[PDB]
């Protein structure tokens, strides 16, 4: 829209590119996402508009939707840093536990809210978790999944990431629930603590086997019905589960306990956001502020 002026490529992804942009009229800085086009499904519109109605302190607000010439522009409230950059800037020092605790608490608050409205994110990753200098963190592109279907690459064709993909999805489950977001969040939580991606797979089979080497190869004992999954293969290598003490050192036992429940193979036993909020780990939760390098 000739009402916005891009300032810098802020992100890249599936749908399209993300830009920091200054509204030429109101003067506000927003985040713009240009998506790519035969007629633009009205279904994607209905659902994109329904997403515009959810307001919570931990979800990046979708100010507006500009459908022009079969091209979609999404205007979002702007935040100053994604969690990925913030992690790289903390690579040597690490993020303090009080801040990690808070971020997790807020992130679960937004999740609890979205989920109670039957809305799920579907593709959480450090790249769409945005923080402000006031100590808050928000979910971005929340629900932008029920707008299309998972392709093969990005706008210019690149590399998405199966690193944060829950196992039910890697295994062919098409009707997954809100639980996939908790799984994603758990991976991110672990990454914040250790400063290294939990499961950096380089293919769908590497992703899966990586989860298997750490949490052990799943079977009907921990995940009933897993063998009926579309992509399950009786011939998967059988790895044993490694203790979390080795996966997320030196996070405390309350966190490890919480992370554990967020990373349970069985989607149904996977703790929900609302319950996660009552976990003992958040007993001494506060709202510390980050030290951002903008
Ligand atoms: C990569 N995909 C992204 N998507 C949205 C909606 C993003 C968004 C929304 C609002 N504010 C910001 N800020 C920001 C993003 C990346 C940065 O590296 C720095 C700041 N980003 S980023």
Image (cartoon, helix red, strand yellow):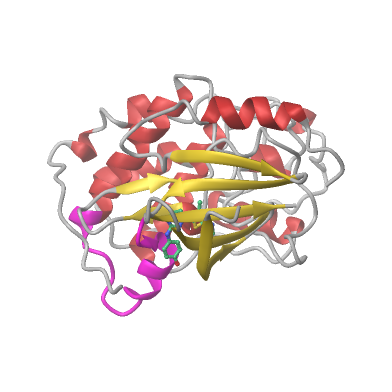
Nearest the eye: 179 or 25: 25
Residue 246 in view in this figure: no
| Residue furthest to the bottom | 92
Nearest the eye: 185 or 43: 43
Residue 156 in view in this figure: yes
> Magenta stretch containing residue 94, yes or no?
yes
At 57% across and 46% down in the image, what residue appears? 74
* Image quadrant in which you'd find residue 2: bottom right
Asked whether, in this view, residue 197 is left or right of residue 246, the answer is: right
Tally of numbered discs: 0
x and y, in percent, of residue 45 in the image: 67, 30
Nearest the eye: 239 or 52: 52
Range of magenta residues: 79-99
x and y, in percent, of residue 141 in the image: 54, 44
At 79% across and 28% down in the image, what residue appears? 228
At 51% across and 47% down in the image, what residue appears? 75
The answer to whether 195 is drawn above or below residue 114 in the figure is below
* Image quadrant in which you'd find residue 291: bottom left
């Amino acid at each position: 829209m000739e009402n916005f002026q891009k300032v810098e490529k802020i992100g890249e992804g599936t749908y399209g590119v993300v830009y920091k942009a200054r509204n030429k009229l109101t003067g506000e800085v927003v985040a713009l996402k240009k998506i790519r086009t035969e007629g633009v499904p009205s279904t994607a519109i209905r659902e994109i508009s329904l997403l515009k109605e959810l307001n919570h302190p931990n979800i990046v607000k979708l100010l507006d939707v500009i459908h022009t010439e079969n091209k979609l522009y999404l205007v979002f409230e702007f935040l100053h840093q994604d969690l990925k950059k913030f992690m790289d800037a903390s690579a040597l020092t690490g993020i303090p536990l009080p801040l990690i605790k808070s971020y997790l608490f807020q992130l679960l608050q937004g999740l609890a809210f979205c989920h109670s409205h039957r809305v799920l994110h579907r593709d959480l990753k450090p790249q769409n978790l945005l923080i402000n200098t006031e100590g808050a963190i928000k979910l971005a592109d929340f629900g932008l999944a029920r707008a299309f279907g998972v392709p093969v690459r990005t706008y210019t064709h690149e590399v998405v990431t199966l690193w944060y993909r829950a196992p039910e999805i890697l295994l062919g489950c098409k009707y997954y629930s809100t639980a996939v977001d908790i799984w994603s969040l758990g991976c991110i939580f672990a990454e914040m603590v250790t400063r290294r991606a939990l499961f950096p797979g380089d293919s769908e089979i590497d992703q899966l086997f990586r989860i298997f080497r750490t949490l052990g190869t799943p079977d009907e004992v921990v995940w009933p019905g897993v063998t009926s999954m579309p992509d399950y293969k009786p011939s998967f290598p059988k790895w044993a589960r490694q203790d979390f003490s080795k996966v997320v050192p030196p996070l405390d036992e309350d966190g490890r306990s919480l992370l554990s429940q967020m990373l349970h193979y069985d989607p149904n036993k996977r703790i929900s956001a609302k319950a996660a909020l009552a976990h003992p780990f958040f007993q001494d939760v506060t709202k510390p502020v980050p030290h951002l390098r903008l």
